[PDB]
Amino acid sequence: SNIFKLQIDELLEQVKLKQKHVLKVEKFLHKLYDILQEIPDWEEKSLAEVDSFFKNKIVSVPFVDPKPIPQNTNYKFNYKKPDISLIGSFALKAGIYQPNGSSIDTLLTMPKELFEKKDFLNFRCLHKRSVYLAYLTHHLLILLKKDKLDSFLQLEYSYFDNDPLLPILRISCSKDYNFYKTRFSINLLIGFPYKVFEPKKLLPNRNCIRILPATPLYNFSVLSSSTHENYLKYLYKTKKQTESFVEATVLGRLWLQQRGFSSNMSHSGSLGGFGTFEFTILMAALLNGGGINSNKILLHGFSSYQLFKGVIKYLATMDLCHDGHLQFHSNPASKYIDEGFQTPTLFDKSTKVNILTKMTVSSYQILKEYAGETLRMLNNVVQDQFSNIFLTNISRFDNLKYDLCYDVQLPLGKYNNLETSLAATFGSMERVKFITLENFLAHKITNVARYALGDRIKYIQIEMVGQKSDFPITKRKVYSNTGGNHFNFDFVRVKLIVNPSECDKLVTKGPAHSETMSTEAAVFKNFWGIKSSLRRFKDGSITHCCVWSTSSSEPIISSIVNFALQKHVSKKAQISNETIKKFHNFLPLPNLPSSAKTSVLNLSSFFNLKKSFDDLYKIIFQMKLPLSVKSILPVGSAFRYTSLCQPVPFAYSDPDFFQDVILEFETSPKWPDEITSLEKAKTAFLLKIQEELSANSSTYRSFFSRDESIPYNLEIVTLNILTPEGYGFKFRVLTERDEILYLRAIANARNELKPELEATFLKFTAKYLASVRHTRTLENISHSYQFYSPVVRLFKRWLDTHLLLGHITDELAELIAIKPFVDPAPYFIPGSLENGFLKVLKFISQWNWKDDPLILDLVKPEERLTLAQYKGIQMNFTNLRNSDPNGTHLQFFVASKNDPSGILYSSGIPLPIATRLTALAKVAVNLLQTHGLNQQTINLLFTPGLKDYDFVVDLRTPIGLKSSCGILSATEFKNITNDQAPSNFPENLNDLSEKMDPTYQLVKYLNLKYKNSLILSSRKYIGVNGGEKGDKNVITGLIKPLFKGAHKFRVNLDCNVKPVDDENVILNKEAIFHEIAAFGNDMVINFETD
Amino acid sequence: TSDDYVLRIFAIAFTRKQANQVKRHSYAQSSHIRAIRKVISEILTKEVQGSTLAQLTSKLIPEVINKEIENATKDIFPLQNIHVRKVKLLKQPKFDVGALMALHGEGSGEEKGKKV
Amino acid sequence: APESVADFERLLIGNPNSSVVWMNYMAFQLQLSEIEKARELAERALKTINFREEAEKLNIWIAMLNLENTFGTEETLEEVFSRACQYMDSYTIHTKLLGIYEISEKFDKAAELFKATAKKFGGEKVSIWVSWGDFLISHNEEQEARTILGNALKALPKRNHIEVVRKFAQLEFAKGDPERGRSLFEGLVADAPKRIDLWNVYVDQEVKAKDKKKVEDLFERIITKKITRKQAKFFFNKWLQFEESKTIEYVKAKATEYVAS
Amino acid sequence: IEDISAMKNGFIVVPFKLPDHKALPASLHFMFAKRHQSSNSNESDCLFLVNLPLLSNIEHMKKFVGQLCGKYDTVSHVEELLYNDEFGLHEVDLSALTSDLMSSPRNTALLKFVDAASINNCWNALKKYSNLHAKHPNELFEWTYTTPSFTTFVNFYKPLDIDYLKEDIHTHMAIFEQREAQAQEDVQSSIVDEDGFTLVVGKNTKSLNSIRKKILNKNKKAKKDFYRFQVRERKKQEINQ
C-alpha cells in the first residue's frame, strides 16, 4: 500500500476546487433563503377556489395520481413560512465536478401546525405538498420577476429521485451576474416535521389506504420526507469521529457514477436505486455496527481506503436482501439479524424507515456482485488496477456493460385503456402495492423475466428509455405522448447478463411430475400453457419442460423472452432486436447437416475433426519406424477452436484447412549435425511414413509440400494427409537437435547478422516450440470461457474485412480476444458475441503502446503469474522499449506465462498496419458512441473501408469458392450446394492449386520482394467476404513516406525506378502494377488508382 | 500439470546385466543412483509439466516415457526395463462440465413425446 | 527548422537508414552536451539501422570515433574501437580513425599506433603507408619517412614493392625531396622501362613538381627507350600539350621520323 | 521524358516492354547497367544490373541477348546471374554457418560472360541501345516472355514428385555420410603436430572444426591467518580500530 495512497491523493487532486467556485453559488442561495425568510404567508384555503386561483394564471399545479375530486376534500390547506435547512452534501463540502452538476440539499421543512395525527393516507398530504410547492414557486417567480434577474436564471419542476410522490424545484440558469461555470442546478425540496408518529403506522408492513397489502414506496417517501435530520446529526458526529468521510464519499461518488448508480430509482425502470448518500449512511452505520456480535466493524481511526474496502466487503459478502439485514438506531449497539425481508433492506430503530427501499432485488443483486468483483480486484497484490477501478466510465456505453439488450415497443395508450392493452391486473390493491402503471409494469417485467429464464441469466436489469423527469411549470405532469402511449417512456429496454454455460440449453426442465399436482407445477402450467409439456428424459424421470427449436442466427433467449412477454405483458408489445441478428451470422455459416438449425456454441465440427485426427493418430502409432514416434500432438487452429469457418469435410480452398500436427521422435543421438542434413533426414522419415501409409491404409492419401515460413532453409518439407473422413493434416517433425542447432548458428554467426538470425529463431520457436504450449493453454481455457471461440471467429472475420490478416498473425488476435475474457476489471466475463466483440474493440482502442504492455495470466476463474515474474515481465518491457524509442518495428508487446519474451507473436508486422489497427479501433468506438448501435451502424462498421491509398487491384479466380470452401451463402435451397460441395478428394492431386486460391502466396511473395518501399495487404479467406458468389479479393497497400516525392538514385535505394530526371528517380507505378498483372493475368481483372 | 491436477507420479527402474558381462553382480555404485534418480525425476517432471492430463494419458498409454528414460539414461548405466507403475492424483481443479464433455463428444438431451 | 527532439524523432522514424540526420540528431544532443545520452542514441542507431547499409554504417562509425575522440575518455575510445573492429571492416575503420586523428591534430601517440597498426596489418595494405609517409613528410620527419622504407621492403613482397616505392616517390616528389624520389624510381627504371603507366605518371609528377631540365631529359629519353605505336603518339599527346600549355619543331621532326624508321 | 540515355554515375538505362493488360493499353521496364569485375573467377567481366524485373532468370537473359544478337549482331553468351537474391531468401547460409560442407550486394544481378571482348561488344551495343531507347520507343530492342514465373511460381501449391525428392535424399545422404565419416576418422587420428605434439581429441568427437570452434568459444584459496606478517596486520587493525 505504498503507491495506492499516492493514487488516492492524485484521484482527489483530479478535483480539488471546493473554495473558489463554491462562494458565488452559496451567496446565490444566501439571497435565496433570505427571500424565503421574507416570503409572506397565507391562511387556510379551499381546493374549489385555489383551482381557479391557479387556472387564471399561467402556473399550474402538479399532482400525485389522481387530482382530488371535491367529494373527499376534508383537509385544511396552509401556506406558511418554512424553516429552511441548507443541509446535506455541500454542507459537508464533498465537491465533485459534473457535466450535469451536483446539488446542495435544501429543504423547506413543514411547520408543526398544518399537519395532524393522520397524515399517512389517501395522499392528501402529498396533494397539500403539490399545491404548496405550486404557490411557493409562483410566489418565487413573481419575486424574481420583480427583482429582474430572469434573463440568466430559470426554474423548473422535477421529481425528487424520479418519483412522482415528490415533485421538487430545479433551480438552474442559462447563458455580470450570469452563473454558468459550476454545478448547473440546486434542488429545493419540501419536507415534513420529525416527531410525527410510531412505527406501526409507519412501517412498510401496514395499510390504511382503501382496497392489508404493503405500501412500501408510500411509507418510505413520507417517512424520509419527515424524519431525515438524525441522519445529518449522525453524519456530523461521524465527521467529528474521523476525518476520512469526505474523501470516502467522493471515492464512492466516483465509483457509483462510473457504475451508473445515481439516486433516481430502480423501481421506475432505471439503473440506479442505490445512492451515494445511502452509501454514506451505510458507511456511517458500519463504523459502529455490522458484526454478528454487533461489533465495531470499521474503527474510526484508520484512513479512507480501509473503511472503503470494509464497506465494499460488507456489502459484497454479507447479505442484506435474502438471508439477513442490519438493524440500526441513530439515537446502543447496531445488530445484524439473520432473517430477511425479501427486499434490499437495513432497518432503523430510531427512525423506522428502510433506507435501501429506493432499489429493488435486481439492483441489489447487481450491486452485490459488483462489490464482490471489486473486492476481488482490489485484494490482489500482483498487479494494481486503480485506473481500472476508478477511471473507467462503463456507463457511457451501456451495451458494453450488459451482455445483451432488447427493446419493448408497446403502444398501450391511455391510463383508462389498460385492460384490453395489457394482460396484467388493475385496481387500488395493486396501486397501493405499487405507485403507477410503469412502476408495477417494471416490477411485473422483472418477475416474468426471472421466472421465464431462471438460472439461464446472471443478472437482469430494466429501464425506460424516453423517460423525462423535466416536466415544465404550466403542465401538471410530464404529459407526453411517447409513441403510442401517454406514459413516460419511448420504449422499454431490457438488459441481461447471461450465464454462458447453459445459455443455449434447448430445453428448460421445470418441476417434476407427480399425481398430486403441486403448486409450482400449477405455476409452470399457468405460466407457459400452450408450449409446456411433460416429458420423460433418458434416465427415466418425468419433468414438465418446454422444447426450443434452436437456431444459428439467434439465441433461444430471444424467442423465450418473445413468447414470455407476448403471453403476459401484452399481446401486441413488439420485441425489436437486430444487432444480434446482424453480426451473429457474420460468422460464416458452415455447410453442415442442419447447421443453420444448430446453435453457435456447438463445436461438433471441431470434435468431428478431432475424431478423424484420433483415427490418424492410432494408425500413425501402431506402425513401425526405425526410430518410433515419441509424441505426436496437434497444434492447429481447429484444434484450438479458432478457425474462422468451422471445418467442414472436403473443403479444399480454405487456407485454414491444412491444420498442422507436429511429431517428435525418440531422443536419439544419431541425428546429423547441420540443419540441411537433419531437415533432409526429417524428409526421409516423412517419406517412410507416407510409403507405409500408402502400403497398408489405402483409404488415406498423402502428398508432400515445401515450406517457406521458417526462412533460409528451403528444404523443410511437410507431408499432408488427406483423410477419408474429409479433413487434411500437415505433419511437421520436430527434433531435439533443432533449437540447439539454431543456437549454434546464433553463437557462431557473424556479428552483424545477429538480429536477423534472432528473427529467424523467433519465427522458429513461434512455429515449433512454444506454439504447443500456446495451443494447450488456450484449448484448456476455451471451456470455461465459452464465447471465446465465436469472438475469435468474429474478430478474424472483421480484421479480414478491414485488411490486416496478410501481415498480422493469428496469435495476436487470439491474445487480444482473450484479454477481456481473462481481465474483467471494468466489466464482466463476456457471455454474448456482441458484448465480447465490442469489449475487444473498446480495449484495443484503449490500448497504448508506450505504456501498456499486454500481460496475460491464462487461467480459469477463481495458475497465475507470480509477483517476481510480473516484475520480470515489467522489467523486460521497460528495458525493451527504453532501448527501443517508439517501436520502429516492435509495435505490440504481448506477454503470457507461455512466453515471457512478449515479442514472440508480434515481431514482423509493419508500423502502418499497426497504426491502421489502432486508428480503426478509435474510429469504431467513437462511431459507436455517437452514431448509436444499430444494424446500419454495424454494417457500416463492417464495410471493407478501402480508404483509397495509392492502389486497389481487383482479383478474379475463375471459380466462386463457396462450394469448395464449404459455407452456404444463406441460400434458401440447401440441395443446390449439397450437390455442389465436392465431397470427394480428387483422383489426380495436381488440381488442388486451381481449386484453391493463390492470392495469399502472391501477396506474400510480393510483400517480401518490395518490403522496403511499399507494403501490400489483401484478403485471404475469400469465401467469407469476397461477395455473395465469393470470388473477389483486393491487393491494397501503402507507399512508404520516404517514397512519396522523388528520390536521388544510388546503388542500394531498392526500388523499381522511373528515371526521368538524371539523378532523382521515382517508382514507376505503371511498371509495378503491370508486373503484378503479368504475375496475375489469370488472377487480376481490375486496377483502380487514387 | 498444465491444468491444476497434481500427481505423485512414480517410476521404477532396474539394472541391466550388460552383454558380454562375466560378474554375477551388476550393482549400481549408489552415487550413480543419485544421478539416475535426479535425471529421471527431471525428465518426467518435464514430461508432466509440458502436458495436460488427457495428453498425459495419451502419452502414458503407448509407454513412451519409459523409452525416453531409457534413451536419456542409457549413457550412465545400462538400465533394464523401466516403468512408471503409479500415478496418484492429489488435488483436482474444478468440474468444468464443458471440458469433460469435450473429452468425449458433445450431447444435448432433448424431447421425448408427452402423449398425455 | 529542426530544433526539437520530437521533430528529430519524427525525421528518424520517417527514414531510419539516413545516418546523416542520425548523426545530426546525435550532434544535436552534443549541442545540448550529453555525451552519455548521445552514446545511448548511438547504440539505438546501431540496433535500428538495416545492417546491409554499410556506407551509412561507416558514417555511424565516423560519428562514434568523432564522439570518443573529441569528448570521451580514451579508454572508452579503445572500447568503442574494439567493438568497431569486431563489428565491421577493420582496415577501413583503422585508416579512417587515423584520418580523424590527423584532422584532430594529435601526433605523439599517433606515430606509435602507426607502428602498432603496421605490426598488426600493415604488411599487406597500402593506405597505412600512404597516411604514415604523408604525415611524416609533412611534419618534417624526412629521416623517419626514409627509414620507413626498410620496414616497407621488409613486410611487402615483390608484387607490391613497385607500388609502395612508387607512392613513396609520389609523396617525396610532392612534399619531399625529388632527388630522393628519383633515386627510388631509377631502380624500377632499370628493372622494367617497358612499363608505361609508371613512366607516364613519373613524367607527370615531374611536370607538377616543375623541374624543367629533368622533364626535358625524361621526355627526350622516353622515345629512346622502348616505345610502340600507341605509346609514341600517347607520349607525344602528353608532350606537345605540356609544352604548348624553340623546342616544338625539334620533336615534330622526330614524331614523323619514327613512324618511318 | 524518355530521351535520357545515361545516368549520373555511369549507369546505362535499359528499359523493356510490357504485355497486354486487361486494364492498361506503357512499354517501359527500367533497368540500370554497369561493367565491373573482381578478383575471383565467378565475377570476371561481369555486369551490374540494378532493378531486375520480377523473375528474369537465365532463360530470360538468353532470350534478351538473342534479340540483341538479332539486332546488332554482337557476341553474347550468358551463363549465370550471381546474387540473384531478389526475394530475400538466400542472404545468410545456415549450412555454411553451422556445418563443415560448403564452407563459407543488394537486389542486383551480376551477370558474367565468356569473353572480355564479348562484354565490351555488349556494353557498347548497350550504350547505343540506350540511345535508341531514348530517341524512339517503337523501333526498340525488346525481350520477350515465355514465363518460368508461370511454369513454377504461381502454382506453388503442388505435390512434390516422390521419385525426385527420393533420389535427392539418396544422393545427399550418400555424400553427407561419406564426408562426415572421413572427417570423424580424420579428427580421430590426427596425432602428428609438426613439433612433436599430440592433439588431445576426446572420445567420439567428430570434427577438428568442432573442437576448434569449441576452444574458441571457451575463452586461489589463500588464508586470512597463519602468516606472521598477516597476523601482525590483523592485530594492528585491532589496535588502530
Image (cartoon, coloured by chain):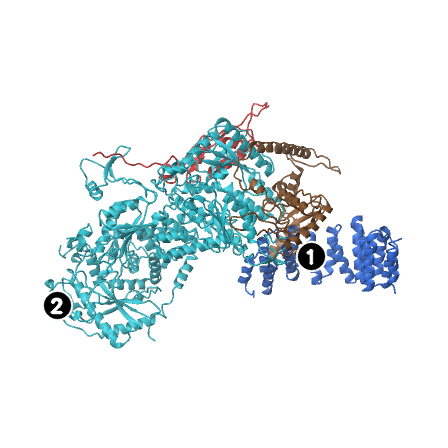
Chain colours: A cyan, B red, C blue, D brown
Foreground mark, 2 or 1, reads 2
Quarter where residue B54 is shown = top left
Q: Is residue A326 above or below residue A700?
A: below
Q: CA distance from mark 2 to mark 1?
A: 110 Å
Q: As rendered, which of D204 and D106 lies closer to the eye?
A: D106
> Which residue, as the protein is rendered here, is positioned at the far left?
A71
Q: Amino acid at mark 1?
A: Lys
Chain on which label 1 sits: C
Residue A319 in percent (x, y) is at: 28, 50
Q: As rendered, which of A540 and C181 lies closer to the eye?
A: C181
Residue A1090 in percent (x, y) is at: 49, 56
Q: How many marks?
A: 2
**Horizontal side, residue A327 vs residue A591: left or right:** left
**Horizontal side, residue A154 vs residue D109: left or right:** left
Badge 1, how many Cα within 10 Å: few under 14, some, many 20+? Answer: some
Residue C236 in percent (x, y) is at: 83, 58
Query: Which quadrant of the rendered structure holds the N terminus of chain C?
Result: bottom right
Indicate the secondary structure of the residue bearing disc 1: helix
Q: As rendered, which of A1016 and A462 lies closer to the eye?
A: A1016
Q: As rendered, which of A858 and C27 lies closer to the eye?
A: C27
Q: Which residue is mark 1?
A: C96
Quarter where residue A396 is shown = bottom left
Indicate the secondary structure of the residue bearing disc 2: helix
Q: Is residue A136 above or below residue B106?
A: below
**Horizontal side, residue D224 vs residue A112: left or right:** right
Q: Which residue is mark 2?
A: A48
**Horizontal side, residue A262 vs residue A876: left or right:** left
Residue A989 in percent (x, y) is at: 50, 34
Q: Amino acid at mark 2?
A: Ala
